[PDB]
Image 1 (tube, rainbow, N blue to C red):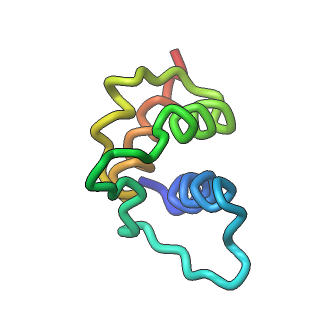
Image 2 (cartoon, rainbow, N blue to C red; image 1 turned 180 degrees about the horizontal axis):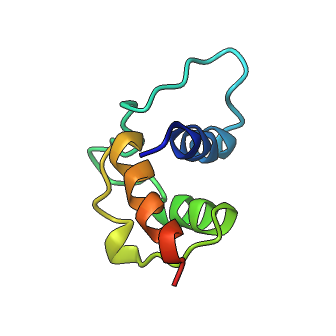
Length: 82
């Protein structure tokens, strides 16, 4: 995944709780980590799919790894965006 995409995705997560000011951003920073799976993925997938303006499915945005894999995924969806 291109750094441009990695930085973008990592941003969508920060906006969730207003971050990116005094916090360190990493592509390995697993966004999904909850023993109860309380985290709202629908909100995340929507942000990325919206900003990037792509067409991703929940099944494709449910088992996505850290930002590393996330960025790579969106990349392919940005190739044809169909």
